[PDB]
Each structure stands twice: as C-alpha cells, then as structure tokens.
Amino acid sequence: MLGFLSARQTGLEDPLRLRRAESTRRVLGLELNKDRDVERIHGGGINTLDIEPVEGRYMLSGGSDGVIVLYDLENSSRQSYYTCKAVCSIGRDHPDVHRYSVETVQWYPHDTGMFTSSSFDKTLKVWDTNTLQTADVFNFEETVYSHHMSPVSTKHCLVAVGTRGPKVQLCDLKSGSCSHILQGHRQEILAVSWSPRYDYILATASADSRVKLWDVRRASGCLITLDQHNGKKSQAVESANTAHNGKVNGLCFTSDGLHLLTVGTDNRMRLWNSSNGENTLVNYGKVCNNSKKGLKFTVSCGCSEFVFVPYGSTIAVYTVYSGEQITMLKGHYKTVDCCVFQSNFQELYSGSRDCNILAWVPS
Amino acid sequence: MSYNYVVTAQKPTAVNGCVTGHFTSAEDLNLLIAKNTRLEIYVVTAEGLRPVKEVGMYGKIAVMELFRPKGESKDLLFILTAKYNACILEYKQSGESIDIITRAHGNVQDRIGRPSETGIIGIIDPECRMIGLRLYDGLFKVIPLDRDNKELKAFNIRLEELHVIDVKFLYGCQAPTICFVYQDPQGRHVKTYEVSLREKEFNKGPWKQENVEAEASMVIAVPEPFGGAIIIGQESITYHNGDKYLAIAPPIIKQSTIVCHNRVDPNGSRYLLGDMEGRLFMLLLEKEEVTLKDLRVELLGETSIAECLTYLDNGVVFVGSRLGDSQLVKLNVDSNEQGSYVVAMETFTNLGPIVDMCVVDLERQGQGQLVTCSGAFKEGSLRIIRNGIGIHEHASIDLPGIKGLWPLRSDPNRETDDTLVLSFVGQTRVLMLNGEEVEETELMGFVDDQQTFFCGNVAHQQLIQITSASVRLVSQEPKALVSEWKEPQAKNISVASCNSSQVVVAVGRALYYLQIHPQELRQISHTEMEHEVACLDITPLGDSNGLSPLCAIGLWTDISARILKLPSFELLHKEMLGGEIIPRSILMTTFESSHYLLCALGDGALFYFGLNIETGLLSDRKKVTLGTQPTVLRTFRSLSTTNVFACSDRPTVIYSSNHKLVFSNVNLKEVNYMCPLNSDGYPDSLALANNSTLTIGTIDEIQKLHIRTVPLYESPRKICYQEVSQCFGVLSSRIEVQGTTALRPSASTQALSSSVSSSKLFSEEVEVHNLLIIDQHTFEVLHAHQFLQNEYALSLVSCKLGKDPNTYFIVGTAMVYPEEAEPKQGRIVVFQYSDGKLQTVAEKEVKGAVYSMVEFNGKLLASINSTVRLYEWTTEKELRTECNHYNNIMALYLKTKGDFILVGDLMRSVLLLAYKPMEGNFEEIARDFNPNWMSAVEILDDDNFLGAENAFNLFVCQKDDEERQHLQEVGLFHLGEFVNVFCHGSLVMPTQGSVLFGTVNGMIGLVTSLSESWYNLLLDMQNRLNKVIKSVGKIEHSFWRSFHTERKTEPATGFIDGDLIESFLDISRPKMQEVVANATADDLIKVVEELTRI
Amino acid sequence: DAEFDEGFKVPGFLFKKLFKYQQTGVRWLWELHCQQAGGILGDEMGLGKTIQIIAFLAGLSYSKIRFEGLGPTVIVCPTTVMHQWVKEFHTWWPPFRVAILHETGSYTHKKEKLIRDVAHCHGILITSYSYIRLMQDDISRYDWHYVILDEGHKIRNPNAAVTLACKQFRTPHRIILSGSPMQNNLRELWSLFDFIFPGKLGTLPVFMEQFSVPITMGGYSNASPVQVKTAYKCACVLRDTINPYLLRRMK
DNA sequence: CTAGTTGATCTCATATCAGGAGAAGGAGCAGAGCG
C-alpha cells in the first residue's frame, strides 16, 4: 500500500487507482464491527433498510411490527465506540403508523426531506421527514410486496409498486395518479427496480418466474423478457422465456446500470445484459433463498463490483462479473431480510428476523 | 464563509501530451505540447523551437490530437478535458493577432459511468470520419465529423468488452475500424470492430480476435502500405494484419515497459518507443514486395523518462517528460562511441512531481526561497526557486553620484566596450576597465570641465559626446576633436539623445536634429516646441538603413508622450498622461513582435504603448506602476533579444516572453543608472551604478523565477531544513535490482561520508531509502545514511524536543515486504548532525508506518498507521508515548498550530484534534464528515483548515451541542492539480497569510486570505471577467472551478481564482471598460497590481 | 421548409398553408410519434383536423424518417366522409395513394386484394367502422403504421364490437380525431384512452373507482362540499394525466 | 354490364324434536416384517 501512496504522490498511478483499490481492499476486509453498535427499537424483524443517497448519513428501517425507525449513522461522539442512535420513529403511537409490516422504505432521491414506505397494509405512504407526518397515501387493492422510486429521474417522480396483483402500479408524485399500470405479468410482482442509467427503464420480477423490462413511457408493454437460455429452448411466448425456475424475488441493477442481477427461488442468481436481457451465464453457484416475499440485496459502488446477497442467516459477497464467492458475513441469528451498502466508507448494514441491525465495517 | 485567493506562482511544467502537425499554417510544422492546463504551440525551425502561442485551457488537457478533415487546409486540434469538455480548435492568424477559434465544443460526460482504469483514450480515424473516445467502461463514445456539428453531439456504442487497455483506428480500412487490446478473465486479446456511423453500432471486424501477451498494453496502427497493428507487450512485440502474424521478443525491451511510441516516418517504417527507464528504442519494419517481412528493435540511447515523444524532423525528437526535464534530442546515424545515437540538444525545465518542499530564508535575506523535492526515479532533483534576476556581481568601484553611464571602445580595432564614461555633477570621468583590471584614466577627445549628458560610439569608427554646452565628435583613429557643433546662442543643453548615426538635442524648449557624418555635424530639422523638453530617444529599431525615422519626446505642463517626424519635427501622435510629475525616461524598444515605446514618470509610473513604423501611433495604452522613485530605461541585448532594465529603487528587468510584457525583479537595493558592457573579461555584463558604487554583474535568465537544479539521480521524498546545522535533510529513494546493485551512481552513493542503519529492532528490484544531508550553500551531499533493508523512510522532521538544546533529524520509517498490504512495523529514528557525521541518538520501534511527524510544542507528534500519538522526549533521550488517538482510517497528514492538530485522513478528510495540556490527552474538537480523500492539509488561521482532495480540489473547513463537532466546508475550488504539499511562506519580501503549495505537475501555487470587502469586490469582478474573457474551448470558468468528484459537484465558493483576476491586466482598454461598468478602472488596476505583488 | 427537432421536415409550401394552431398540432403529433404513443386531436368541429393529419403524414413520408418514411396507414371514418378524406388527401398531398375500402370504393375486385395491395404499397386505406368490425380478420394481419380514427368517439363504448376490433391493431401510432371525445360520461374517455395508449388510465374497474365515481358524484346538486373538493382533486389529477395526449383547441 | 329500390337482419343507442340404513373415506392404532 505504501507502493500505492508512492505511485499517487509521484503521479505514476491516477488517484482513481488508489481510491478504487483501497475500496476493494476495504470491502474484502469486511468483518463484524469491533467498536460499532446500532440502537435496537424494532420489536420484529427488519424487512428493509435504506441509507439516503445524498450525504449517506441517515438510515431508514422498516420492521415487521410496522414501525419505521430513522437512525443517524455518524459518530457524533468523540469515542471510537458508538451506537447509531435513532433520530426519529414512526412508532406504534404515531397516528399514521403502518398497521402491518413495512416491507420497503426508500429515501426520496435528490433530497432527504421526504421518504416513502410501503406495507402489507396495502398502503404506500409518503412522509415528510421534517414534520414526520404523512404527506400522501396511495391505497392498493392488494398487499404491496415492493416499491421503488427512480434514483435518476429529474423529470418524472413515479413510484413503481409491485403488489400481489399481477399489475405493476406507477404512482405519480406529481398530480397523484396511481391509475397507470403495466400488464404482462401473471402472478405477484415480488420485486421492482428502476434502472440507474436510463430514466424510464423499470425492471419487474414476479412469481411467474419472469423478469420484464419496461419503458414506462411506451404504450406497447415490456421491452425485454429475460430468458435463461437466450433461445436454446425457444417457444412461442406464452409460458417460456422464464428468468428463473422459481419465483424471481429480487432485482438489483449494477452500479453502472449496464447489467441486472436477479435472484430467484430456484436457488440461483443470474446476471443479465440490461440492454437486450441476454444471460451472461455468470455462475454464482447456489444462492440459497426461499423467501416468499421480495428479497432486498445491493451491489457495491466505487470499487475496482461486489454483490451482497442475504444467504440464510448470512451475507454472501460475490464478484458480480466473475461470480467468485468472496465470503460469508456470519453474525445474524435468523434469516437475513435486507442488506444496504454505504458506499462512502464501504460499510454494510444488515437487517434480519432477529430484530437486529448489524453493521459490518472494514477491519 | 472563508475568503481565499489562489494564484499560480509557477505554471505547471510537466508535459502530459504532445503532437505534431500543420496547425498554425499549412507549411509550418508545429509541436503542440500539453502541459496540464497550458497548451503550447511551437514551430519546428531547423534549429530549436520558436514558440508562437501559449494558451490556458479551463481544463486539464486529457486528449490532444491534430487532424485534417477533407477540404481543410491545415490541421484542426481536438482537445478533451479531464472534465470531458471536447473542443475542436483552429488556429486563425490575422496578421499580428493570433487567435484560437473554437470550431466546435461540447461536454461528453455520461451522467453515470465507471471511469475506465487505463484512462481517457481519444483516437481519430485517419480519414477524419469520426473521433472515438473511451471514457468509461463498456462504452465507446463516437463523435462523428463528416456531419459538421458545432455541439459535437456524441453517441455511445456499447462495447461488450469491458476492460479495454488500448485502442487505435486502423489504417487502410473501408470503414472506420478500431483495433483494441482488451482484458477478459481468460487473458488479453486483440479484437477489431468496424464502426458503422449510420447504424450507430459496431460490425464484425476485418480480422478476428487474437490471443496476445499477458501484458500487451499498447497498440500501434501502422500506415497504409502495411496496415494492421503492432501490439507492444511487456516481453514481445507482435504484428497483426489478419493473416500475417509476426512476433519478436527482443530481450532488450524486457527490462522495462514501453509507455510511449511515435511514428518517425509517414509510411511507418520506423517507430520510436520510450520506456519507463528513459531508454529510447527504434522499431523498424523491413518491407518485402507490399507486405512486411520482419520487425527489428534497436536501442538508440537514453533520454528523460518520456511520457510522450514526438519526432519532429532531421532526427530531432521532442521527449516529453512528466517526471524530468523535457528534452529535445537528436538522432545521429552513428553512435557516440558509447552505443547511443541520442544526443540531447535542449532541456526544458520541469519541476516534476513536487513531492515535498520547504521555504527557507536562505542567504539570510528577508526573502523565502523554495527548495523542492522535484522529479522522480532517475530524474530526481532538488530545485531551488526564487523570485529574482540575480545580479551576479563581479567587481565594484566606489564612485559616488554617478548620474551617467556609457560604454566606450577606446581601442579602435576592438569592437568591445573596453571603456566607460561617467558623468556625476559637472564633469566627465572615464574608466579604462582593461580586462578585469579597472582604473580611472582620461581618454583623448573628452572635456573634463563640462558634464556628459550623453556620449557613445557611432558609425565611421567615431565617438560622440553631448555635454551641457556643446557636442564633441571625437575622431578616435586620426586625432582629437575635428567636428564640433555648438548652439548659436550658447544656451545649455537640457536633454540629449543619440544613436549610431544621428543626434537630437534639447536646448530649453527647442530641439535640434544633427546627423553624424565623417568630419561633419549637419543640422537639418529644428523647432522650438510648446513647453520644455523632458526626455528623448531616437534609437533606431529595425534600422536596416542606418537611420531611425521617428522620434519620441516628453514635454512639461502638458504631461504627454509625443511623437515627432524626424526630418521635420512635426507632431505625429499624442497620448495624454497627466499628473504633476514630468516624464523622466522615454525609450522605444522591440519586444519580440514589434516596436513599443516605454515612457516613465518621476513617481515610478511607466507606460508602454504599441508603436508603428509608418504613422507612429501609440496604441493599446497600458500603464504599470513600478517603484516609488524616478526611473531610467537602458537597453541591453542578451542572448535571446533586447531586454530593458527599469533603474529605480525597485530595479526591474522588463522584457517580453511569449508575445506579452512580463516584468522581472532585480533584488538589489537601488540602481540609479545602468549600461550594458561586453569587455574582453566581462561578457554581456552590466554596470549598475547606485549612489555609492558601480557593481559589474551579469544576469542569468530573467524568467521571474530563477530555478537552480541539484540532480540527485534518485527519487527524493521529503525535505526539511536544519538551520543550526546549515543543511537540508532529504529522504531519497533509489531503485537497486538484484546481493543488490545500484543501477547508476546516485547522489546517495556519491556522498562525502556515508553510513548504514545498524538496528537491532527487527530480526526483482528493491527501493533503498537514505537520509541525505545536503549542504545548504553548495548543495553537495555531505552525508548519506542508508536505511535498513526493506525500510521505507516516509516522514522526516527537523526540530528540537523536550528541554535538551540539540536539534534533531527525526525520521519515521516503515518496513515494506511484498507479502503485506499495510506496514505492521516501522520505527522512529532520532539523528543528530554534527562533525559531518550523522549519529543515531535514539530509536523507538512502533507498530506501523509513521506516515507523518510534526514537532508539537517540544513533543513529537507522529501518526502511526491509524493512530495519532504524541511522544515526549525524556531526559534519558528516548521517546515516550504520552497520549493516543485511534479514531482514524489512516492519519496521513498532520499539521499544527498551537494546541490544535489537523489530521488529514486517507478518506475521512480532516479532524481537528486538540491536545488539552492540563489532562494530557487529545480531544476531537471537530471533524469534517465528508469522504474527501486527502492529499495534503494546512492551517491558514486559528479557525481555517485548508485541505487538498485527491480529485484535484481544494476545500477549506472552518470550526463551526453535537452539531458543533461538524467542520463546515466553507470553501470549495477545483484546482485541477494534485497538491502534494502546503507550506507557509512566500517568495517575496490587503491579503492575510500566505500558504505555498506544490503539485504533481510542477505548479507552485499560493493561497492567501482576503477580507470580506476585498473578496466581495473580486468575486464580482470575477463574474464580469467571465462575461468578457472568452475561453479557448468556450468552457465556463464556473464549470472549470466547480468542485468536482464522482459523487459530488458544487460550484466553487469562498475562493478567488487569482489567475482569472490577474488576467485583468492583459486586456485592452475597451474590454476593461466593459468589465468595470457598475468605480473607475485605474482603481481596479491598483487592486490587481497590489494582488499581483503577493 | 420547416425543420423540427430530430429529422422531421414538412414542405414549406404545405407548411405555409397551415395556421399557427394547425402547425402546433403537427408538432404535437410528431412529438407523439417520437414517443411512440397515440393521441386525440380534440380540436372542435371545423377547426381543421383532416388537414393537420394530412400535413403530418405528408411531412412523415417526405422526411424519410420496417417502414421508410410512411408505412401503410388505415383511416377509419364515418361512411359519409370517406370521399371527403380522399378529396382532402388529393388536394393537399397528391403523391399519396388513397384507396377506399367500401362498396362504393374504386377497386372492382376482391376487397382483401385491396387491403393486401395497400399494405404492400404503403398506401392509405380509408375504411368505415362497419368494415373494420366486419373485416377485422384481414384488416389486422399486415402491420399497419398508422390507425387514425376520424370521429373516434364511435369507440366510446368499451364493449362494442367496433371498439374491440379497433383495439386489435398492433401499432403504437393510434390517433383519434374527434372534437368531442367525451359525450355521456368518463367511461367514454377511458375507452378512447385505452385505444390510443392502453396503459395511462388503468383497467376500467380501477378508472371507475378512482375517477368516475368521485368526479361524477361531486357534480350532483346535493353534493357535500367535501365531496365537491374530492371531485375537484380527481378532475385535476385526470386533467394532468391526459394532458400530453389530448390536444383540444377551442374556437 | 349496371346502378337504384325493397326486404330481412344485426348493432347500437336513448333513463332512471319422534328416520333409518347402508356404503365409501379417512383416522388412528396395532402389529408384522425387513432393511
């Protein structure tokens, strides 16, 4: 590493080299945090986490008990040991608390003054973070499994919602219009994710073992349907062209948005060319998941790319483009529901059914 | 909010890219050199390089390629900036005026994308059908050129190979074909695609992928007769044309990797190849009838470590170095009897990577003097930089009240100035100065009872003298006075002027024109003007005949610089100057382009105008205020051109470089008079008269910054000055290969005395690290203490600790073994320099690399890998831990002011630590919680902490319940340089404080604090100059200085780009008037001049 | 010539005839074409919608932007105005081949041959709504480029056979010309917007529950003030939702 | 050939406790029998 510093000082290597190499080295040295703790407030398992995209300081967490906790991750104390204190809380005494489990919570991109939370109580609530009051509510005829706002859209502010209905709802923040729907799936839509690269590209994964990419501006259904075999087993499109041999319960675009990682209940993760949906045939081995709802997993950013997938009661870290298994982060006592990656310091926060949020820091 | 003023003391000198072509004209051969933000356009003459233009981009020039579209007469220049401003520039010369017009421009940044590892590649189709840009992984950006854009609308083609090493456009292809080496997990392969501009996608290339060397890193597209590509790898050079596959593995290129290449010929039968060691190879393609028969590589010789190299013509190669001085070398057909055909013709100074520096008030003056660890591996050196011309005096004669100096050739045969005439109050004094001997003698033909207003050598092997009463034309060869002219009314002469042919004398309000002829003084033109005369000059410029056709005068009570028609003494032009002080000096001089008229007042004001040989009309008035005393201007022809010396209480050498007037200081006390002198012993020497004596010195170069060079031949790393010992401690590093062997005699291996580290604490090519003690007068390596095997000396501090009186050199080291990523071992060694030897006074084995040390109130503050600890120096002379702080990723940079410690982290960016002395432990005052990767830190005030981010940004944090622990970045600024060092001090004798900084490219910049009043005024001017000055790539200044990182971008704030402000003097009056719409302009000249003085 | 954003040129002599609002409509139609979305030229009766469509198609074929320029388009209009469309096309853009699929017609052979000829010749097939219902087997096998429906409010009944027939065209470029694209209730608006852009207003049950009951029930005389405000809320939502795809200029 | 008249037929649109008996399945236990 002194070689890295010397090369940076002498201009031999771009500082990009040291930055990304050290980010990768930090991610590889991920371990149970020696001096860090997260305050425990959820009475039930944490189903979702979200660190705000700008300044990466505050973290939302939705629990199976319906409460939403807002933590400050910064060590505002002077000690080397600190607990990520809870700033705010939609608790059981809040007038607008979710009646059932919160399954997805997401900070509004471009601004930390608002966030959103969807629950199995058939509601997507939009909260003002300052007053901590519901600015808007979007009711659905069937329970919400996931939702996502575009991390890129300066123009549109649509929330793509996947419920147990076979339709992907698009709730417009502007002129409150939840009527827009996308047809083409056949069972519950367990995951939805906007492309970080393209403004109007949305990937949706449903229990019909299919993943569809939509240009929501378009009037002609999905753009691409992901196919495991790319055409080896080709059939008229009524039941073929499946992404997995089970329910596809997790989506994650890579950092650049040029590839898509789909995890399904066939104990398989697959990497897809996001421009034509071709399977890249990256192996990843066997990725154990049996979750009946959406599975939240994230990818690394700003490194020389990693994907952190909940794997039983562990976090499996894989190399996205080679599939090589890095490691198992092993500190949870029950199945891990979500993991969210802090890209500023290569940190990880994992929420599981054991009512714990565990922080993994580079050693 | 904080108010800071950043300015460039030394422009970047490291050459990141150079191309050659016909840019300035269809017939000229240009060498365009990109230094980081400066673009230098040269013309390749038969000898050397004649600069024509130097423009400053608002951008780091990442790509630079010359291309000739169909129909274009001369090359256009494509520039891509690091911030991805693309522009196509054309050179349009309109007579005297030179412009760089932006034929097109745009911004090609994709909103997201992984910037590619190998870096920005920009290639152009040889038929100029498109520009390919590889900026990000997985994409290949295409800018079509047949479609004449003005916005360079660019489109991405998804490139399925995500790690492309290098790419070129192949030659002789029906369609634009790229050939690239890319890395996939199975190895490196060379693949080809054809780019289809209409389908906006790739198509199958002419020749299939080929599996190549593991480190194949360079692709050379070979011109049309051959076509195909040459892939240079670490160990082999391979050639591909689709069916032909030649390969050679010359052992001679195995020692180092080839990093730059260049095609010597137009048909590519020969290529120059530069490697990281500085060797220069010639790759030859031997043809057969046409196909290619075989490849050869031969080692031409050695150069500076080339970043880029260009073949100009006639064997002349420009070697562009980022790490050393760039070179202009020659390729001889035959060896120099030592195996090398390379012969260095010229060397261009490069303050290479300035890795550390100190400002030492060496010479015990009041002026700082930077001493920089510049350069790198073979090119390492210490550069000593000062803002002075450098009198370099050789003799003196204590003669008081010398009001006149003129060089004389008393010996007829000699053309040398071997005599000097002097006027003091009322008489004339001659000095012989034969060789080095100086004496006071009398020369025939001169009156010692009347003062000498002027005298000099003239044509016809004649001398001439203008005294207060008459003029005496001395016939040097035959005898004493034979032609003498006396004013008919016996009125005294008030002012005189003369040249090699003619004369113009002022008597009262009247002017007389005399022409010197053999044994004759003929009066022709005469007049009695409006007011008294003040100053005159008739020096012919671009004479070519023997006579000057113009005249310059200064008058009284109508303070103005007038021009006259010599044969008739009519009034040609008038520029009104004003004031209550009469003009004192008027001179007309050629400054690199044309004729300028320099007129000065008695208050140090000085006006330079652009004069014409036909009308005599002064244009582009610009005024500059030098000195607080009267000035006189004397002309001396140096090696290059004429340079004028403003003689005053602030003597200044005013010359022009790069077609602009830049003023160089001379740092002696005062200079009343000067005259040039070239005696048999004194070449191109001066003769500076002051009130007391006559100092006889030469001036080396007049470049504003004088740069000495102390070649170390090894990479220096740190430098600290020990005044009591009169030496610099310099940590150096040399690369030895095998037990081990030095590849060359470095300064460490050639010390007076030496020593080796014998420590009991810890029990290819490797870096040997030494502590060099360097004499601060002669800069010879007095001592070289070599450190342990596998020990990296990182930090070095000079200080005295505790209570003992000795001054110590304290070195912090780390143990580097290839099996590890972070040193776990390291030590702090305390040395004392005495009796020319370096004894080891103490040691302290620590458990990490000691990245930084600062002496902290008599205690030693070191930063071991992630812990910052304070050591006490016990009476026992050992270091004892006192307190620690552990809350860091890696404390790389430490600074101090009082009880506060600024810790720059590798990536948490600053933490204001306070050593609370009553308790004896550290306390985190505040922290900046942004993830800025630091390169240096500094403390400006009690509450301002400057930091340099690794993305070429400067930011200022300011000490702001728990939100009081958040330092606020109140200043943001994209510098465009990778700052390596901040240091308090200034190179010179409104603004508060002064922090110098050195960069990787060789910029030396200077940060200073402004007040709110000044800051507001200058920010408003900055906005208006952006509204007025037109940038080369039509880049916005605000965009250029916007704080930029891959995850953040903000407009600058709290920072004044002093460069943009100081460009306010380089604009003509109408544009200036536009700038200052809403107080008067001369007021802002006061401000900007006062700012440039810092 | 008039040059629009990317590659669309409409001839100068043709452009000059059009009024300001008509060429604004041509601009809007081509923005829809770029978006590959349908629309409703809601300009009232007499403002000129045949001319706007003719000019836009003329500029689309002229601009040379599967289909090079203009493909085979089908115009469904009431029986009384088929020859009107023929006359307007002939006078405004005579280069187009404009055949009528009707008993009156001009062909004098098997109709299916006429549809085949127009499909393979990239001509304009003007037909009636009754024929679209009757010949839905043949009319949708040919990959038409434009399915302009003149007086497309005939599609207002979502369950009528004509509506189900007209909603079989695969192309995205669906245009309705009707100066009154709402006549009895919001179900009609849903039917039309299902034709031009199937997704915006969701499934008919959802559209009913979200818009029809709130907006309609707040217009009754006995509406409570809160219910009136809810209807206002829903009407504003719907107006914002349908703004980009409805171009309705008044007289 | 070839247009105009005549009937049939379809679509679409206009509001407001005092049974009993037997057969088929599944359930739980019990044991036998073999790896």
Image (cartoon, coloured by chain):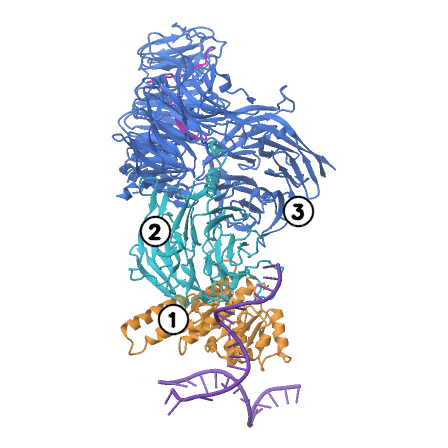
Question: Residue under circle 1?
Answer: C210
Percent from the top left, x then y, of residue B95?
Answer: 48, 36
In the depicted structure, whether residue A139 falls above or below residue B633: below
> With A53 as the anchor, is B166 left or right in this view?
right
Percent from the top left, x then y, of residue B829?
Answer: 41, 22
| Badge number at residue B208 | 3
Q: Nearer the viewer, mark 1 or mark 2?
A: 2
Give the residue displayed 40% in from the left and 70% down from the top. Answer: C249
**Discs 1 and 3 lie in a common subunit:** no
* Mark-to-mark CA distance, 1 and 2: 40 Å
Colour displayed for chain C in the image of the structure = orange
Residue pushed farthest right? B289
Colour displayed for chain B in the image of the structure = blue
In the depicted structure, whether residue B623 falls above or below residue B203: above
| Neighbourhood count class around disc 1 (C-alpha, 10 Å): few under 14, some 14–19, many 20 upward | some
Q: Residue C179 versus residue A76: which sits nearer the camera?
A: A76
Numbered disc 3: what chain? B
Is B312 included in the stretch rendered in magenta? no
Q: Mark 1: which amino acid?
A: Gln
Q: Quadrant of residue C156?
A: bottom left
* Magenta region, residue range: B653-679
Q: Nearer the viewer, mark 3 or mark 2?
A: 2
Q: Element at badge 3?
A: loop
Numbered disc 1: what chain? C
* Mark-to-mark CA distance, 3 and 2: 60 Å
Q: Mark 3: which amino acid?
A: Lys
Give the residue displayed 54% in from the left and 42% down from the top. Answer: B122
Colour displayed for chain A in the image of the structure = cyan
Question: Residue under circle 2?
Answer: A40
